Image (cartoon, rainbow, N blue to C red; front, side):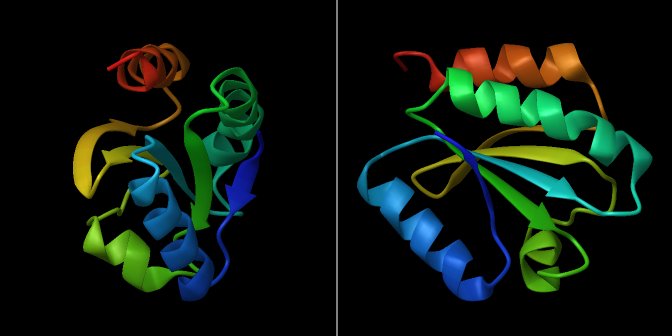
Length: 111
């Protein structure tokens, strides 16, 4: 299991429909290349994706896929968004490593 970098609206679509069919948790890192705390959270996110291979970990650049950042009103980065079967379960705003880790544990958990 790896972080998928979601570059196009098509990859977004595929990744979301497939996870929803499988009823998997989706964790999304809304990120920006210029964003210091974003670069810093990259390896943390990557490590959680390895540790929870039954959740789908997505990365979305807020500058590249504006409509996706916008539908979730993401104007602070990094923002970690937790979603399952269409519902937003949770969010972490900023490089808060323990808060990200805890909510992945809680939401990936044998529900």
